Length: 330
Image (cartoon, rainbow, N blue to C red; front, side, top):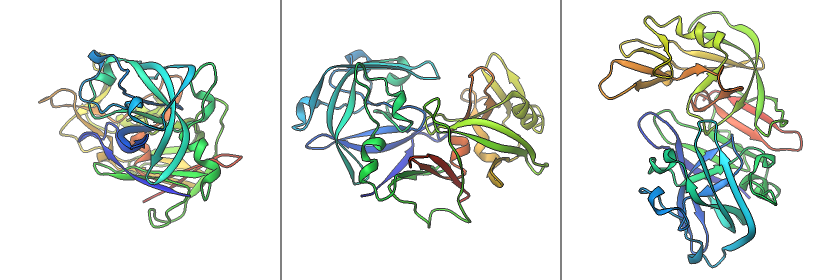
């Protein structure tokens, strides 16, 4: 089997992408944030504290003839940005882009933190990291991809995120028309539960490529590119007037600037992020200070190849027995 679903930016900055997901019978379609940095499929629901729902579409398990309470199971997750959610668990039929999994754990939120409430466009998350990170207790549950894997034509999914435009998540096949050149594959460590890999270096603009190993994760659920402070300083040094602002929370730059590209290495291959992808717009409406899309990871503990990086590539998440990542230009 295969599936193919369009993913759409939630706003004009590409802060996140939502993908429609069918849950239950008859289908309830929710728009979920596919997140290769986490491993829970959780949704706003009829159980979510009413004051914490503000415009999201909810899953109502009592209206699904295939829903079953997973008795005794609870979940609670905290994300790198300080947001969180928790609740109980149903199993139900879940379909993405025509690919159906029966008995998928659908984690129903009883509580969500304010950042989720405040984002009316995201009805929940669909985790695509390794199932070892799933938070359901006392019986850990499998991700949608892990449940689907055995049925797929090939044990892979691909992320093809758009710049200020829709893109595509495919399951079970690699669309050879969706990229240029060849796909370069690279080894993955699953030791932390992430799609963790090592980039071979970087370049700023037309500058020389610096060969250096940068371990990080491929994370579709993170907006920006978070890299070591040395790398990030070298990038922003090429933008007149750019500076790191502790009060704003990162590097800012004059909105009048033209940003240089940023290149990262995948083996001997190179993925070029155009400068425009690094512009996240005014820090507040009407400001002439703009927020940068490349930021330091120093306060995180891990480097993160988020959407800024991934949307410059066609990305293969190969979930074979020995997982690998593939990157192609597009």
